[PDB]
Length: 48
DNA sequence: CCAGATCGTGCGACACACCGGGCCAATTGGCCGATGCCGTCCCGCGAACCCCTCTACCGTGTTGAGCAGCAGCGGCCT
Image 1 (cartoon, rainbow, N blue to C red):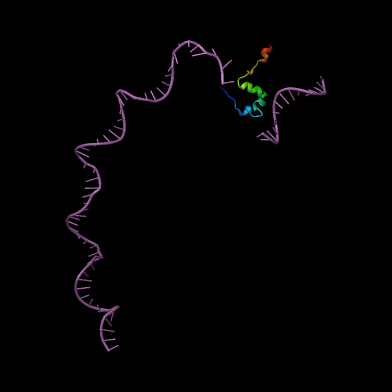
Image 2: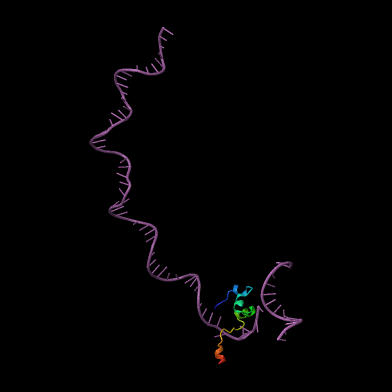
């Protein structure tokens, strides 16, 4: 299974957080299997 | 003065100088040929060597200092 690099996750400032605009707590929750993340949504289909 | 050392000279011996002959001793050193023991290998069996599998009373919780970013809150502004 894929894993993350600790240098680009933990070190302040959280580079992943800055790039994706995620607070470090949310990122830590996601990567360490504590909450889901929505990675795709079909806006036009649901609106129709 | 004059007689032996030194040297001249002479006669002989002569130890080889030659450069050429004519045979030989010692001493071979090869493996010739024949005989014999060891290295390698191909099984043969067996001791051990490692891996996998299953057992059903039941049983249910682990210092100080320096610098920077984030969360909560007081208080405008709409």
